[PDB]
Amino acid sequence: TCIGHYQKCVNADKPCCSKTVRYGDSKNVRKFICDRDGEGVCVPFDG
Image 1 (cartoon, rainbow, N blue to C red):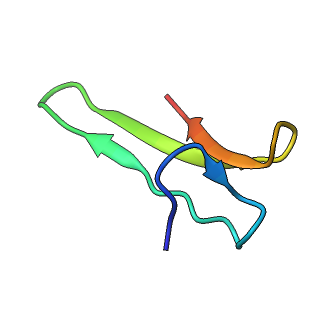
Image 2: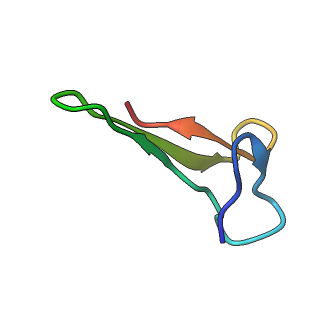
């Protein structure tokens, strides 16, 4: 129930997965929002 990355968000609710990698002391969480200002597509965010 979520799109990968850089997809069209003008054909559904707001499907956008997320990539939260790990390692140890440091942690990076990649988010994906739905932007309409551009071409109405879901792109990476956060971090």
